[PDB]
Amino acid sequence: LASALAQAL
């Protein structure tokens, strides 16, 4: 999940 969100950056 962290990666799924972190893509924003």
Image (cartoon, rainbow, N blue to C red):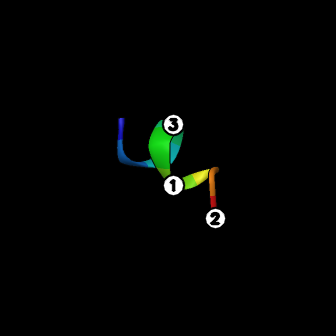
> What amino acid type is highlighted by mark number 3?
Ala
Q: Residue shown at 51%/36% (left/top)?
A: 4
Residue 4's disc is 3
> What amino acid type is highlighted by mark number 2?
Leu
Disc 3 crowd rating (10 Å Cα; few below 14, some 14-19, many 20+) is few
**At numbered mark 2, what does the secondary structure look like: helix, strand or loop?**
loop
> Vertical placement of 9 versus 6: above or below?
below
What whole-number distance in Å separates the C-alpha atoms at marks 2 and 1? Answer: 6 Å
Question: Where is mark 1, residue-wise?
Answer: 6
**Would residue 6 be found to the left or right of residue 7 on screen?**
left
| The C terminus, quarter of image | bottom right
Where residue 8 appears, as percent x and y from the top left, is 63, 52
Instruction: Classify residue 1 by image quadrant.
Output: top left
In the displayed image of the protein, which residue is found farthest to the left?
A: 1
> What amino acid type is highlighted by mark number 1?
Ala
> Vertical placement of 8 versus 4: above or below?
below
**At numbered mark 1, what does the secondary structure look like: helix, strand or loop?**
helix
**Would residue 3 be found to the left or right of residue 2 on screen?**
right
Disc 1 crowd rating (10 Å Cα; few below 14, some 14-19, many 20+) is few
Q: Are marks 2 and 1 in contact (CB under 8 Å)?
A: yes
Q: Residue shown at 51%/54% (left/top)?
A: 6
Q: Nearer the viewer, mark 2 or mark 3?
A: 2
What whole-number distance in Å separates the C-alpha atoms at marks 1 and 3? Answer: 6 Å
Question: Where is mark 2, residue-wise?
Answer: 9
Disc 2 crowd rating (10 Å Cα; few below 14, some 14-19, many 20+) is few
Q: Residue shown at 47%/43% (left/top)?
A: 5
